[PDB]
Length: 48
Length: 48
Image (cartoon, rainbow over the protein chains, first blue to last red):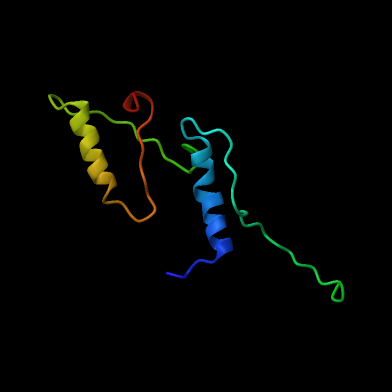
């Protein structure tokens, strides 16, 4: 429905799916093809 | 917390004559009428 971007999808999977899948019966390692959201502080050296 | 998600453990039992299976089957139907984003699960004796 084009309401979620690549980054939005990766966050939801990492935040609501990965942990439970990684603890599911017979599952070894789980590799996320993306990254969970973090609070990004993008600094400006001119303003600093 | 239960399986990594916030939870609230609820104990209870079947009424005189009625079985555990019947009690659990009703709780499942009561749980399906709860607000959006609220799931359920069985633990301990109920898991077995």
